[PDB]
Image (cartoon, coloured by chain):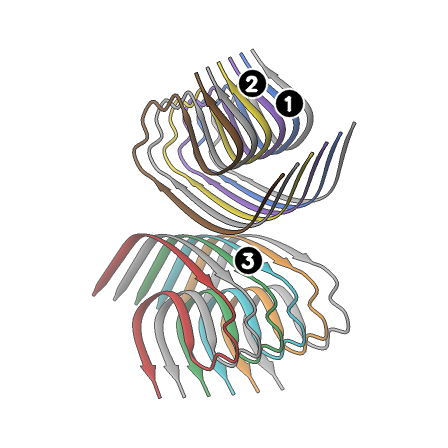
Chain colours: A cyan, B orange, D green, F red, H blue, I purple, J yellow, L brown
């Protein structure tokens, strides 16, 4: 079990052209890339 | 079981042309890229 | 089981031309890209 | 069990062209790259 | 069990072209590269 | 059990072209490269 | 003459008990405290 | 003459008890404290 | 004449008790303390 | 004439009790303390 | 004339009790202390 | 004329009690102490 709390996240992104993947600020769980 | 709470997220994005993927600020669960 | 609560999310997006993917501020569940 | 709390994260990204992977600010869980 | 708290993280990224891997600011859990 | 707290991390990255591995600012857990 | 434009401001405040002063997100002009 | 434009400001404040002064995110002009 | 543009500012504040002065994230102009 | 542009500023503050002065992240202009 | 651009500044402050002066991350112009 | 650009500055401060002077991370211009 995951207990994630009290996060202050600021995400700046620039350009980001032809993104074919995942761009996530805060991710809880699992990321599978194929 | 996931328990996510008390998040203050700010997401800035610029440009972002021809995005074919997922751009997520806060994601809970699972991301599969194929 | 997922328990997500108490989120303060601000999402800024600029440009974003010809987006063919998913642009989500807060996502709970699962994202599959194909 | 993971207990993650009280994080102040600032993420700056520039360019980021043709990203086919995962770009995450804060990730809790597991990342599998294939 | 992992207990991670009270982190002040600043992440600067530039260029980052054709990224096929994982670029994470703060990661808790496990990273498998294949 | 790991107890990590009170970290002030600043991460500067430049160029970073065609990254196929993991670039992490703060990582807690385990990294397996294959 | 002041020309202020194109500002994206996010202001988070917590607690803030018995405030006797001015708490302003974006202020243009002049502030006099006495 | 002042020409201020294109600002992305995020302001986090915590506690802030019995504030008798000015707490400003973005201020253009003049501040006099007495 | 002042020409200030293209600023990405993140301001974290904690505690801040009995503030009698000016706490500003981005200030353009003049500050006089008396 | 001052031309200030393209600044990425992150400001962390802790405690800060009974501040009678000016605490500024980015300041353009002039500061006079008396 | 001053031309200041392309600055990546991270400012950490701790304690800072009874500050009667100026605490600035990035300052352009002139500072007079009296 | 001053041309200052491309600076990556990290400033750590601890304690800093009863500061009556100027504590600046990056300063361009002139500092007069009296």
Both labels 1 and 2 in a single chain: no
In the picture provided, is B27 more to the left or to the right than L10? right
Is disc 3 placed on a helix, strand or loop? Answer: strand
Along the line of sight, which residue is nearer the eye, D17 or D30?
A: D17
Q: Quadrant of the C terminus of chain L?
A: top left
Along the line of sight, which residue is nearer the eye, F6 or F3?
A: F6
Is disc 1 placed on a helix, strand or loop? Answer: strand
**Image depth: mark 1 or mark 3 in front:** 1
Q: Which mark is residue H30?
A: 1
Along the line of sight, which residue is nearer the eye, H33 or L27?
A: L27
The residue sitting at 42% across, 66% down in the picture is: B2
Residue I33 in the image: state x and y as whole percent: 52, 17
Q: Residue furthest front?
A: L1
Dot 3, how many residues are within 10 Å of its Cα: few (below 14), some (14-19), or many (20+)? many
Asked if the residues shown at circle 1 and circle 2 are in contact, with their CB atoms under 8 angstroms apart, the answer is yes
From mark 1 to mark 2, how far is it between C-alphas?
8 Å
Residue J9 in the image: state x and y as whole percent: 52, 46
Q: Chain of mark 1?
A: H
Dot 2, how many residues are within 10 Å of its Cα: few (below 14), some (14-19), or many (20+)? some
Q: Quadrant of the N terminus of chain L?
A: top right
**Can residue B1 be seen?**
no
Q: Which residue is mark 2?
A: I32
Q: Chain of mark 2?
A: I
Along the line of sight, which residue is nearer the eye, L31 or D27?
A: L31
Q: Chain of mark 3?
A: A
Residue I26: quadrant of the picture: top right
The residue sitting at 46% across, 88% down in the picture is: D34
From mark 3 to mark 2, how far is it between C-alphas?
34 Å
Both labels 1 and 3 in a single chain: no
Residue D26 in the image: state x and y as whole percent: 45, 63
Q: Which residue is mark 3?
A: A11
Is disc 2 placed on a helix, strand or loop? Answer: strand
């Amino acid at each position: 079990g995951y207990e994630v709390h009290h996060q202050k996240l600021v995400f700046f992104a620039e350009x980001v052209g032809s993104n074919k993947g995942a761009i996530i600020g805060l991710m809880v769980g699992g990321v599978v890339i194929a």
